[PDB]
Image (tube, grey):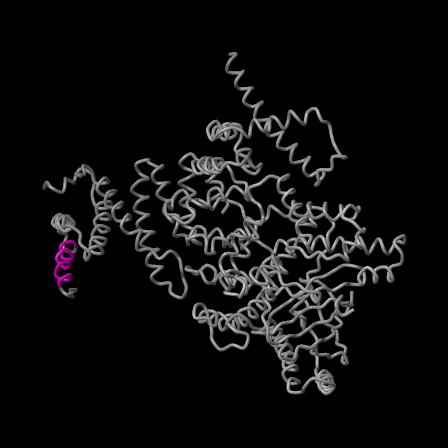
Amino acid sequence: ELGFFLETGLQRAHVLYFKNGNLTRGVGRFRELLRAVETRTTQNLRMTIARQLAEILLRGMCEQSYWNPLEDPFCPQENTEEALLLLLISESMANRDAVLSRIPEHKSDRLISLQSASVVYDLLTIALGRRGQYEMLSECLERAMKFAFEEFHLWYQFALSLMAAGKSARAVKVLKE
Amino acid sequence: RGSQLHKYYMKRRTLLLSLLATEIERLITWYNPLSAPELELDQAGENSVANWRSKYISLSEKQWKDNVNLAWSISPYLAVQLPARFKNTEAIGNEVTRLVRLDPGAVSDVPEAIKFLVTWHTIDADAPELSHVLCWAPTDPPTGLSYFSSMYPPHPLTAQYGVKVLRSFPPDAILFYIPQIVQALRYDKMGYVREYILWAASKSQLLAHQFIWNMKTNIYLDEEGHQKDPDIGDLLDQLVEEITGSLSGPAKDFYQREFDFFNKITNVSAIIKPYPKGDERKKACLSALSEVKVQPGCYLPSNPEAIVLDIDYKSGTPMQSKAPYLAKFKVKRCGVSELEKEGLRCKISWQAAIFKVGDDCRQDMLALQIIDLFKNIFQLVGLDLFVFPYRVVATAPGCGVIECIPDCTSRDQLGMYDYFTRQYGDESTLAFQQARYNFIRSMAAYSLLLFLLQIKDRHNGNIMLDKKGHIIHIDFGFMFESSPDIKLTDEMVMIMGGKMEATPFKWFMEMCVRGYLAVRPYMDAVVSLVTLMLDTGLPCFRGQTIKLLKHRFSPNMTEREAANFIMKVIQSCFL
C-alpha cells in the first residue's frame, strides 16, 4: 500500500550522488526516474525531482555540456527546451491542487501552495525573460492572476510584463492598483 | 470614388432615420398618456413616420445582424446602447455579446456593459478565461450581490469583484442594505463574505450593532423558538460570539449601556404580562413606567439618526388583540456622524412607538424597502406622489419595535363623501379642493403599488386617514401568495367628480400611467432583492413568484402598448 523506507532507499542514492559531486550519474538517474510512467502514487515524487532537475540544469552548467536523454555524452535539443517542457507539465497538473484563498480558519496549506506557485512562476519568468519572449510570459502571468488577492509581488510582475510587451492602458490600470 | 461614398452615406442615412423615428414615437407617447384625439399634432409627417416604422419592423433576422456590425464600426458605445432602444429580436443581444467577448477592453462604462460579459454562460459553468474584471468600475450594490445568489455558480473573480464594489460605499448605504448581507452567508463557499463582515464591523460601530441585532434575531426559526436552523445556525452563533468582546474601551461602554437599557425597557412588558385586561393592567404598566430609569446617551434603534431626551411617564397603554404596549418619547434629531461623536465621547420632537411580542416583522421590512425605492425613483424623475416609510425593526424572535405616525386617525375607527363635505365645506372652497388633490395623490400611488405587489385580502381596517387628507395602508403581512385586482367602490368615485368623465378622473388616469411608465425599468433590482430573500422559507415564497413578477412588468413591449395595457387593466378593475 504505502511503505516508509522504500522511498528512503530510492532517494538516498541520489542524495549521496549530489552530495559527493557525482553530478553526471545523479542527473542520469534523475532522468531515468523521470522516464518511468506516472501512476496515481508518484505525482509528488515527480514534482520534486522535476523541480530539482530544472533548478540544477538552469544554474549548473552551460549549453555545450548537455545531450539528449536517450543518448549519453518528443526529443528536446537544448536544455531550456526540456526545462520549459518540465515547467509546463508541472504547472499544468499542479493547477488542480489549489486552495483558492478561502482562509476560513486555516492558512498554512494556503501558504505552502502560494510558495509553490511563486517559485514555479519565478522559474518560468527567469527562463523566458533571457530569451526575449514576452507575449507568452504575459499570458502566463495573466492566467496565474487567479490566486492573488492582496499580494504585491504578482501585481508588480504582471504590470512590468504588460508594460514591457507593448500594451499600455492595462499596464496603467494595474500600476494604479 | 463614387459608389463607395454613395453606399457609405446611404447606410448611415437609413440608420439615422430609424433611430429618429423611434425617438419621436417614444416622445409623443410620453406627451399624452391617453389617445386624446382633441390634443393632436401635425398630421402630414406622422403618416410617413408610421409607414417607415412598419417598413423597418417588417425585416428579417438577416440584414439585421449587420446593423450591429455597422454600429460597432461607427462607435462601440452606440452599439452597447442599441438594445436599450427596444427592437423585438434576440439576435441583437447575441451579436453584442459576441462582439464584446471578442475584445472587452474597448468598453468600460460601468452600469450596463458588464452584463454582456459577466455571463460567459448562465448555468453551464465552464470556460474560465478572458475574465479580467479587475479593470471595471463599481456598480450599484444590488447588482453586485447577485453574484452570491442562487443564480450564478460560485467563482473567485466574481467574488473579488463583488467585495471590491461593496468596499466602496459610505456606511449609510450598507446600513440600508444590511438584511441581505447576512442572508448572503448561506452561499459563502469561500471566506470573502465573513471577512468583509468582520472588517466592516471593526470599521464602524452602528453597523456592528445592527449586525448583532440581526444575527441575534435570525439565529432561530420560530418566534418562540424550539428548532434552530440546521444550515447556518452554528457559524452564525460562532460569528455572534466572535464579533463582541474584540471591541473594547468607549465602544464597549456604549455597547453595555445601550444593551442594558434595551433589556431593561424590554422586560417591562413581560413583567406586566400576568395582569389581565382592564384598568389594573394600565395601573401596573404606569407604575412600571415610573419605575423605568433612563441613562443618558442611549438612542432608539428604529431611528438611529436621533438621540432620546425623555419620556411621558403617564402614557403607557396596551392595545387590544401577548402584551404589546405603546410609549411616547421626546427626542431630538442631530444626524449620523454627530451621533457617532456623541456616542464615542460619552430640533426636538415627540414620537410614538409600539412594542410587539409574538409575531414576525420581516415581510414588512421587505415591503418598506420596496416602497422607499419607489419613492426615491418618483422623487428623482420629478413627479408628485406620496408614500410614508414608517420604520420597523425586529430585535428578537417575535419581538419588534414599530414607529408610529403622530396624530393618527384611522378611517375605520373614526359616508366618506358626507364627512369630506361637512369637514371641508362646499365644493367651491379651497380646503375641499386641496383635500381632493391630496386624496388623488395618495390613491394613485397606493393603487399602483398594490397592483405591482399583488397584496390581497384587504379590508377597511388597514386604511389610516391623516388630517391633511392623505391615505396610508398598513398590515402588508399577507403578500405575494395569499388572500378585483384594484379596490374601487362608489364613494370615492362619487367624490372625485361624480363620473369617469370628470377632470379629476382624467388626472388620476394620467398620473397612474406616468407612474407605471417611470417605474418600469428597475425590474432587475426588484428581482435581485426578491430572489435574495426567496430562500428564507416565509409562508409567502412558494417558488413560482419570480416568473409572475417578471411577467407583470411587461418587459418585451413598447411604450404605447404598455400604456394601453395599463389603461385596460385599470378600466377592467372597476367592478
Q: Is residue A39 left or right of residue B531?
A: left
The quarter of the displayed image where residue B84 is located: top right
The foreground one among B520 and A75 is B520
Q: Is residue B128 left or right of residue B1?
A: left
The foreground one among A138 and B561 is B561
Q: Is residue B378 left or right of residue B174?
A: right
Total count of labels? 0
The verdict on residue B396 being magenta is no
The quarter of the displayed image where residue B207 is located: bottom right
Q: Which residue lies furthest to the top in this view?
A: B2
The foreground one among B126 and B194 is B126
Q: Where is residue B285 in the image (x, y as percent from the top left)?
A: 71, 84
Q: Where is residue B428 in the image (x, y as percent from the top left)?
A: 90, 52
Q: What stretch is highlighted in magenta?
A: A6-18
Q: In this view, does B175 lie above or below B563?
A: below
User: Quarter holding the C terminus of chain B?
Assistant: bottom right
Q: Is residue B395 above or below residue B73?
A: below
Q: Which residue lies furthest to the left in this view?
A: A72
Q: Where is residue B538 in the image (x, y as percent from the top left)?
A: 53, 65
Task: Please name the predominant secondary structure of the magenta segment in the image.
Answer: helix
Residue at 38% in and 44% down = B129
The verdict on residue A17 being magenta is yes
Residue at 45% in and 45% down = B119
Q: Position of residue B92 (x, y in %)?
A: 49, 35
The quarter of the displayed image where residue B352 is located: bottom right
